[PDB]
Amino acid sequence: VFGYVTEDGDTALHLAVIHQHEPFLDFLLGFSAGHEYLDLQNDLGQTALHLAAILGEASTVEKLYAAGAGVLVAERGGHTALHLACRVRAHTCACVLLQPRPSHPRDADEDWRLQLEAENYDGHTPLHVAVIHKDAEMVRLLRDAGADLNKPEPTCGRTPLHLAVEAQAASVLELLLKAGADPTARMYGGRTPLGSALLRPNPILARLLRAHGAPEPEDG
Amino acid sequence: TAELKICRVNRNSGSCLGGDEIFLLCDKVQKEDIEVYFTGPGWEARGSFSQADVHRQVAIVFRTPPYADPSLQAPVRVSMQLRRPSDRELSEPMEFQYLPDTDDRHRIEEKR
Amino acid sequence: TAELKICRVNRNSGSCLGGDEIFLLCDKVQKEDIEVYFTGPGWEARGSFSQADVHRQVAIVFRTPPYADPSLQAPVRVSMQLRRPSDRELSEPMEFQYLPDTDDRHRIEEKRKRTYETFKSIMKKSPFNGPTEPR
């Protein structure tokens, strides 16, 4: 098995995606399929999948995924390939990942849903990231994928709804609300999304929470 | 008596080697009668800080203690909580994740 | 308007792209009448936070603003200080250093250029031939 690596820890695979060379990629994968070679992480902890996700190449993510690339592997910041997709609005890439791996590679615990609650070193799951980045489209894919809409992040227990309020992303706040995110959740301090929205500028946010049965805040 | 409560921290993860500085916001405490108590299955340890490190009794800056296993190969979740030596009271626990050492450790130990 | 004083910060440097969360410990302030003012020669900006981000009026958690130059190629020292819109009072300045940004997609691009020759080579030596001959 080939074993070349750059000073940055990038193997021939990493470079195939870095250079966006589908033909050579196909060649490499011709053998790599099923091997541990696919999951090798360069010095940033990134695998070829991670690179493909960052580049937002849905076609390249499928090949790697079809070939058996690990979907839970995390790079330096604890980001899985799905986490990275949620940072660069790579909607189509997330879609490829959010379903059972393709059957067979390409010759002309196997629960993909474990990606949904994977947490990075910032204590963020993919949904948190999608909301932090006010990515309504990504929130929709995650929702439909079955992501936990009430999952609190660990610095102060903010739920997706708290993050949307901080993000002043009303449309995201609404998506979460219509999908049933519990507006009664409070962060470690005791503050709720509404209570948080009141101390925020954009009036829309408070209106929404109100309209969706969010109880009124308790003084301060 | 005031209740012990951790309102917020700047980070919830760190190296299993300890030494990571953490900024912790909490409800009113007494600087000479407070500690940061870390626990896990069969493991206990406290954060490192001095009284000067307690800000207006509503914040503490401390360094995390090293984890039980220095050669951790996968993230280990533990509990972090405020403790009052006074009456042995404890705040509600907060998650903290210890992580493997990057480079040198395990790197020179069949990895790199 | 007693006094404005920054007692401690969790970090004094960050990406020129802004967005780094800072934990700032200070003397008593008024959450509705306080801001974090960043300044440099011919440049000013505020930290990003809400009244809900001020804890017991003695600490503030905020994100740093993007620096004037996004393509910074070397560390730039600037000043950070508390500002009270009330009477425009300012605390003593604290140094903060903006650094060249390490973006993912861009980090990849520079890695691409730096590895062009190497890549051409590895596949040249490999049993792999090359793309389809264009008729």
Image (spheres, coloured by chain):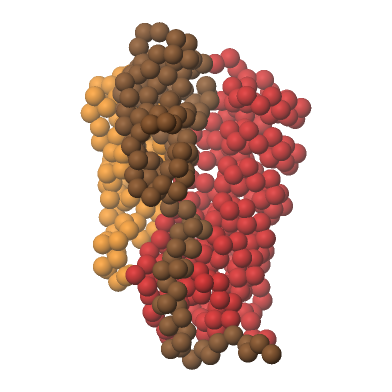
Chain colours: A red, B orange, C brown
Q: Nearer the viewer, residue A161 or B32?
A: A161
Image quadrant in which you'd find residue A172:
top right
Q: Residue at x 75, y 39 (%)?
A: A178
**Is C36 positioned to the left or the right of A204 in the image?**
left
Residue at (28% x, 21% y) in the render = B31
Compare residues B73 and A168 and report the one nearer the observer. Answer: A168
The residue closer to the viewer here, B43 or B98, is B98
| Residue C61 picture quarter | top left
**Residue B67 in view in this figure:** yes
Rendered location of residue A132, percent (x, y):
58, 42
Q: Please, is residue A38 above or below residue A94 in the view?
A: below
Q: Position of residue B2 (x, y in %)?
A: 40, 17
Q: Which percent across, then down, holds residue C82?
A: 40, 21
Name the residue at 35% across, 30% down: C79
Residue B3 visible in the current orientation: no
In this rendering, the answer to whether B70 lies above or below B21 is: below
Q: Is residue A144 above or below residue B32?
A: below
Q: Is residue A68 above or below residue B102?
A: below
User: As drawn, which residue projects farthest toward the top?
Assistant: C1
Residue found at x 42% / y 56%: A76
Q: Position of residue A186 (x, y in %)?
A: 57, 29
Q: How many numbered marks are there? A: 0
Q: Quadrant of the C terminus of chain B?
A: bottom left
Quadrant of the snapshot with the N terminus of chain B? top left
Residue A112 is left or right of residue A50, and the answer is right
